[PDB]
Image (spheres, rainbow, N blue to C red):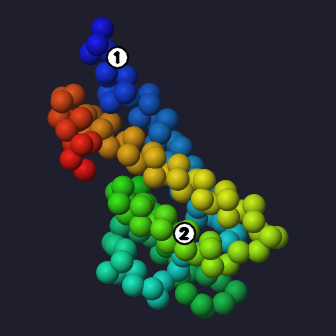
Amino acid sequence: DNIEQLKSMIGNDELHKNLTILEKLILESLEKDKLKYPLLKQGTEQLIDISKFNKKNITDADDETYIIPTVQSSFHDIVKYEHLIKEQSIEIYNSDISDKIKKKIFIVRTLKTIKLMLIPLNSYKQNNDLKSALEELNNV
């Protein structure tokens, strides 16, 4: 049935739960890292919105504070965060660490995909309307 096949993509609770688990895992792996790029002193307020992010402090030196996404960050926040990740990775690049930069980039792309997949599911969970969920995906 066409309706029960569309509900699998934009109205599934199991897909919702699993996507949330993976998002939590990726964020918790981004915070407890070893290499900690993008940090402040760029635009970072007119450039990126700090009200949706989460700042932490670097130890062993009081250089600056680096940025971390949150569960409430939207899609374009993650777009800009990926821009900053890529700039900071291109800056400090050695062949010794060239295998952690790649992991960082891959999991940030995965976050960017998970947010877009979660838009229509979050729209449907509290409205129960398929056309409105698709139109919300199209809108933002």
Residue at 17 percent across and 35 percent down: it is 132
**Residue type indicated by callout 2:** Ile
Tell me the CA gap for discs 1 and 2. Answer: 37 Å
Crowd rating for badge 2 (residues with CA inside 10 Å; few <14, some 14–19, many 20+):
some
Give the position of the N terminus as an image quadrant: top left
- Label 1's element? helix
| Of callouts 1 and 2, the N-terminal one | 1
> In the rendering, at what x and y percent does residue 104 appear?
62, 60
**Residue type indicated by callout 1:** Gln
> In the rendering, at what x and y percent does residue 136 appear?
21, 42
Residue at 31 percent across and 21 percent down: it is 6
Q: Which residue is mark 2?
A: 85
Name the one closer to the observer, 15 or 105: 105
In the rendered view, would you say 62 is above or below 136?
Answer: below
Residue 38 appears in which quarter of the rendering? bottom right
In the rendered view, would you say 107 is above or below 12?
Answer: below
Residue at 46 percent across and 46 percent down: it is 113
Q: Is residue 106 left or right of residue 115?
A: right
Q: Which label number is shown at residue 5?
A: 1
Residue 72 appears anywhere in the view:
no
- Label 2's element? helix
> In the rendering, at what x and y percent does residue 110 appear?
53, 49
In the rendered view, would you say 27 is above or below 127?
Answer: below
Q: Residue furthest top?
A: 1
